Length: 291
Length: 291
Ligand SMILES: Nc1ncnc2c1ncn2[C@@H]1O[C@H](COP(=O)(O)OP(=O)(O)O)[C@@H](O)[C@H]1O
Ligand SMILES: Nc1ncnc2c1ncn2[C@@H]1O[C@H](COP(=O)(O)OP(=O)(O)O)[C@@H](O)[C@H]1O
Ligand SMILES: NC(=O)c1c(Nc2ccc(I)cc2F)cc(F)cc1OCC[C@@H](O)CO
Ligand SMILES: NC(=O)c1c(Nc2ccc(I)cc2F)cc(F)cc1OCC[C@@H](O)CO
Ligand SMILES: [Mg+2]
Ligand SMILES: [Mg+2]
Image (cartoon, each protein chain N blue to C red):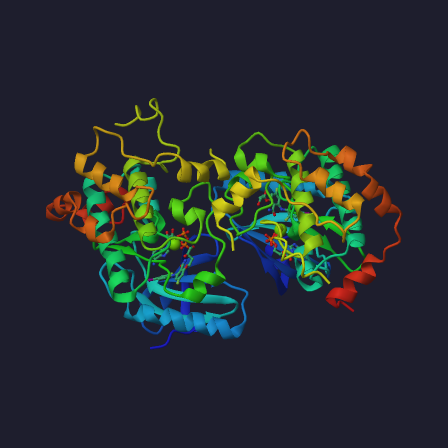
């Protein structure tokens, strides 16, 4: 059935980035609890139907690695995208309370992301455009899912400004021009993994004294680092050699040299992670206390 | 009297940046129309009183070049700052409908800004930290006023992320580290003036063919320009030699070499503008249609 503004009821606020706030809501007619993202866009009515219209392909975005879509509509200056509520939140949140995420777990995470990106590529011909820990969502059934991918050309445009937060996951080629594409998602994924593995955003990399503890930076400074200095890497010793190479292949500067989804899929790390018997569901609650 | 949440009534939305929306509101008990800025901040209660407390010095910020302050309070996840409603909007808005702002007018603008920055310096020991066309506000009485200056240390911190919009007014030294201070406001002012004088954000500068018509860029690309390439400048011929030097002295890269408020105050351009008989009030409406 169609989703309409007054059919919803606010339960709590799930958080905010810039551009959007997201609420936990009850769809009164179905009883379903969902997550409603609201984007305040001061834009003409012609284009705002094109956005709604371009968001409808999300109805055909069915994968266990992609957040579910319920519907999209316009009301009171804001676009509403209504999604499956992920009760585990985003990996940036679980990182905060975890402190650090084990290699084992990041194994299962890496698989979801690669498979998610692959689904979007093959079935829908789109790149993500914003892979970072807060666009990777988890739940109590142990699912790991992507959202906030760039389905709508016109939405991408109307929101065009981006991310100055003292931290950026954009690939060097994306930071330097328009000559970029899907390979860029691999860079972002690689950098997210190193962050989650290490406990902190990994630039500048931990100086010798700072990696001891294992039991800010200005805008131009940070960007210059990304584009001009050698990429981040896992510390040796405490992570497996296969994981180290895996992230190493993700964080190669030259996007044509960088590994692509085809190659990461059949990587030793993924093959080793896929076999492993990991109770993610159990670990997720043990750390964030959902039960 | 004290300002409280339920004493207000929404009239219209004056716009949004990121971090805040600002509404045109009626303070029901006084009848006063004011502008209410709302900042959504997910922050502990101890610090949020420090913010309110640090915003109270705005009660002593009385200058004809500074937006008036009515009060500040916390309600429902958001800090509210209530200001004098400037019915002319911001100079970024008047630029859009003006197309271009005359030299004469920018004369009167430059004076307000310098005098505003000077007031904040001498009487309050603060730098602005965000001089750009949308933090310069005008009204039907012909007033030109600054707001959104950094009065509250703790607010500055809690909002710490900034400006990625394909356009930045931060000085080179501010983009490259923490070694910056009040001189940085001069850079921002100089760049705002060149924008308003020219009709478009002035980086990259107009190539020979593009300055003919007088009757985008990636993040790192833009920043690298600011810090590493020679600064923007007025085109010759269509602006006075005194204005040209004035902006030239504002946009010097080295912050110790850059002109300071003391020097711009007694600059030929300012002395020439101060004498001039300009009906700003009249021009403002002639262009935006307020009457
Ligand atoms: N479908 C969802 N289910 C549960 N939580 C969500 C969902 N979508 C978003 N969130 C939460 O909302 C927060 C803010 O989302 P968003 O507006 O996209 O900002 P950002 O991703 O930049 O933090 C996310 O960090 C996440 O915690
Ligand atoms: N006191 C005010 N009176 C009238 N309009 C205002 C006032 N303060 C802000 N505005 C309007 O609100 C808009 C958005 O303000 P803000 O949240 O500071 O975002 P930004 O300054 O980044 O555009 C401004 O561009 C201006 O048009
Ligand atoms: N940011 C979004 O939420 C977003 C978006 N949202 C979105 C997509 C799928 C699902 I399931 C849930 C969602 F909410 C859909 C778009 F088509 C473009 C978007 O954002 C575009 C800007 C980014 O590229 C960089 O910030
Ligand atoms: N942005 C603000 O609105 C803001 C602020 N607001 C503010 C100040 C004076 C008046 I009269 C009206 C106002 F609304 C007061 C502060 F103390 C810090 C601020 O912002 C800090 C961030 C900026 O430095 C960079 O974005
Ligand atoms: Mg998100
Ligand atoms: Mg402002």
